[PDB]
Structure formats: C-alpha cells, structure tokens
Length: 127
Image (cartoon, rainbow, N blue to C red; front, side, top):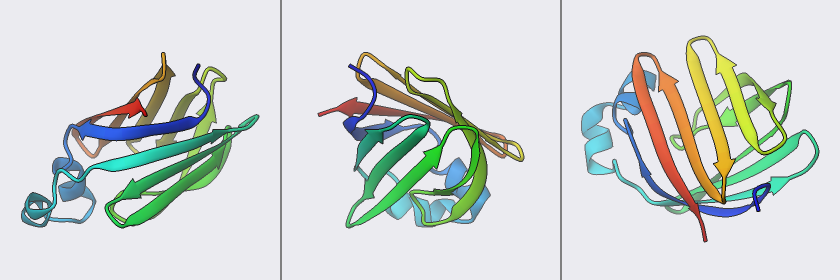
C-alpha cells in the first residue's frame, strides 16, 4: 500500500543533463553518474518526509503539501519549491521552470523532473 516506507533508487534518466544544467559538469557526473541510493518516506497528513541516501550521505526531503519547502538535491543544493500532495501520494512541486512529479502507485515510485530543458525519470522500488 502506498503512503510511506523504503523505496530504493534503481535508475534515473538525465542524471547528467540535470547535473550539467544545475552546476555539476558532465565529466564530474561521468565519474560518479550512476550512484545507487535508498529512499525512506514517512507519510503524515500533508507533510511528507523523504529520506534519500546518496552513497555515504543521506539527504532528506521533508515538505508539507501546498507549502514552499526546501528541497535537498542528490547533489547537495537546497531550493525552495512549492509542492502539493494529492493524498494517494502524488507530490508535485513547481520552481521556476523546474517541474517535479512524484507518484506512488502499487509501491512503485516514478519521479519525473524537468530541469532547464532536460527530462528526468527515476525508478524507485520498495524494498
């Protein structure tokens, strides 16, 4: 059942374009592009807590629907974006031209971001 729990990062699209647009150069990405991570989410009314681990460093992403909250990226940059949450755990946040869609269906998670002009899709699977 979808709400909270651990869903592990398996794969993503544009882990380089996304980085390349935001600050990290593709070559710096290249050396470290396809890092596996783990996500642990706590579902509480409006307020969704996301724990996301990058290698050694776990980078948290806790936000309340309909609120400007600071998003900590897998890179390390934290940004204010207003994210709303459906209920069946759809998390959609908009910042400038950055569109982040997180949808949990059947305990399988797809995160889709658009960064600059880049289209990013991540597969996260519950453990």
